[PDB]
Each structure stands twice: as structure tokens, then as C-alpha cells.
Length: 80
Length: 384
Image 1: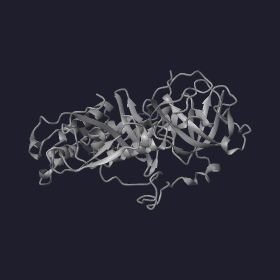
Image 2: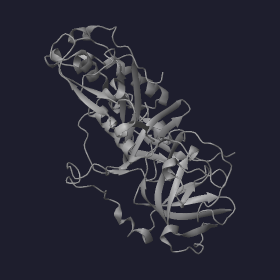
Image 3: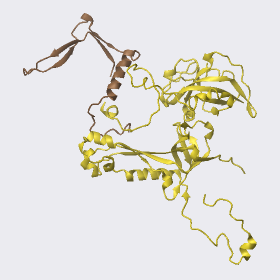
Image 4: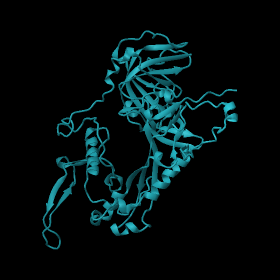
């Protein structure tokens, strides 16, 4: 659950799969060495960037409009 | 109502010597049971009885609309509903009675008596909240009230067909409380059994939300690491300096500095002092009272006090003040304050241009609104 920043994360689109069917998906890679500024940084909760990340997560959770999980809707019972 | 005064006086001579003698027993009218006073427990447990007796999903999810619902939406539709009984219509008409108290473990008001307790929502009058701390402990009688019952259900019905089946209503919770106007109630002070103080006035800007908060390590005092507890705090501005108990009244203020910073203050309520939440409202002046020996720096500032505690969202602020669990507040409405109180009878509302606009996504609003409907929301509840 940590808030995280990445530096110079490479981005690479697929266009083919191992059965030689064309299909599209976007890969993400942090290749070896800190060259070109590559690295990671564990973000503290004090910075407004982390506030914005958490806020966008909260917004995407509330105004979500996706299909509801936990179809067995009797499961929770709150902090039982 | 049933027997208004003015009946003729009983004359014994006539009662004995009249030929067709008339007396309170001679001619009478049979009486239909006019009213009864329930123990608050039997009222509460009539609520939690009629609620589940009348709860039928096939009336809440009608046809043909219900035919097109997936199970998730079906149960989300069914998972909250409300009932309003108005028990004064029952035969015999039930009459609510109990001593009103403010429960310091929740801040909410309660009607209480020897049989239990019932949460209540008093209103002073239509569109004006209960504002006066002096009602604590009075015996409230109300015979024109609403008994509300909120029902929470965690059903698992697959489709409209199974709404005839019993086995799927896996959990049921009610939440019965009462609500009425003070104008419709009669209020009596309970008699007593039979057989050294400083005060100050202030106006409050606005009142934070009542919720569980954690606190900082005390400044200038023992560093007892706090833990979450129910609390709130109020922004306000002192009026005048400290006053002293003076027999039938409060003496004139001690000299008070004019500095604005010395006027504006954060009253911090936590612990058993939370019982004052329901009475404080913005835009009115309250006379806080502290019993005990008159003491400098009692209201002028916190400055330094034993195990002082500021919440995290209020840490470090200079003009904070922990209200002690044995202090009390009195509503003040004297005419000399009326021009400041002219803010009352009106409530701040932002414009529909402040709302409903892309101008900003970082600021706060206030408005009046009728509620159109309320339902559970699942993504923030369980899905994510």
C-alpha cells in the first residue's frame, strides 16, 4: 500500500503474442542501472503530490460506476 | 379536553334531597380509552416489531421494473428503507413522556426514564434548531410526534422470483428514534427532593464535525501519548473579559486586551464535555461558566495546563482552550447583543455559480436542500 514515485520508467507497446496473433497491451520497464535517471522513491504522506494521488484514488473509488464486486452481498457484517 | 372546568359545583343538600337527584354517577357517558403513557422500552420494541412485520420486498421492488435487475442492483435497492409510524394515531393514542438528557458518550439528545432510553431529534421551531442548554433534565411531554424506523438489510436475493422466499434475508438491523417540535411539546421542571466561579461570553464562527479524533502529546505537561476519541472543536471570538460570580448575577468584566488574536479562540470539546454538541450553533452568543475559585489565565488562554491536548488538525495553534468536563454553557439573548445576533434568522448559502462549476476543485460550500432519496453505495463499501 505504499505511495511510490518512479523515475524514467520506460513504456513499450505490444502488438503481437506468442501465438502470432496481433494484440495490444502497454508494457512498463525500469531497466538496469540508474542511467538516464532511473530509480524509485518511496513518497511521504506530507507532500501534496501524495495527497493528490490519494485523492484521485478516493475519487475513482466513489464516482467509479464499475460493476460491483462481492456478489455475496451478505459477507461483510462490518467490524463484526 | 375531555372535562374542561366550569361544571356545576356539587351541592350535597341537592344531591341528597332532589327528587330526580342528579350526581356525577346519575348521568354519564361511556369513555373510549383516550390515551396511555408507554414505557420508552415498549415504544422502542413496538417500533422494532412493526418494522419487520411490514417489511415485504415485493412491495419495495415492484413489477415490471424489478424484472430487469441483476442480483447486485436488486439487493442494493433493497438494502435500505425507512418507516414512519406516527403512533399518536394508534388506538389508544400513545403519549411520549420522559426526561430529556444529552448523552456524553455520543453527544446526541435522549429521552430517558426508568425503562430505558430513546434517541430524539428536537427542533425549537420550523427551520430553527434547539439552541438552549437549559432544557437539560426537564420532563418533556409530547403527544404529536413521529416515530421513525430506519431498516438496514443485507439480503442476497438472486432475482425478482426469489422475493417470495424467506431464506435470503441474512441480516436485519433497525434504528428507531423519535422526532418532534418543541412547540408541540409541554415541558415541566422536575422538583427537587424534599421531606468560587468565573464566566465569559463568546460568539462562535463555525463548529467542526463530531467524529473520532487523535491528539498530540501535551505541551508543557506530561507526555501521555493520546489515542482516538470522540471530539469536536469550535472557532469563536470572546466578548468582554472574564466575569465573576456576583450573587444573583455576574460582575463586570476584568480588563481585557483589545488584540484580535486575544479575542478569537478554539474551544476544544473532548470526553464527557461532548454532551454540548447538540446545543451550540453558529451566529449566537454563549456565556461559558467555569465553577471553582477565580483564577488568572482561566479563559485568557490555555498557555500551560495539565495534560493539555490539541488535535492533529489543530496542533500548535496559540488560542486553543480545553473546556473541562465540569464547565457549563448558558445561551445569552440579552438585547445589548441583538445587533450582532442579527446574523440569525438567516443561514449562509453559496451561489449556484460557486456550485455546479469547474472554477475550482479545492474549496468548500454550504447550501439548503431537500433530500430526494438515499441508498447504500457499494464501491466504497466493499468493491474497492
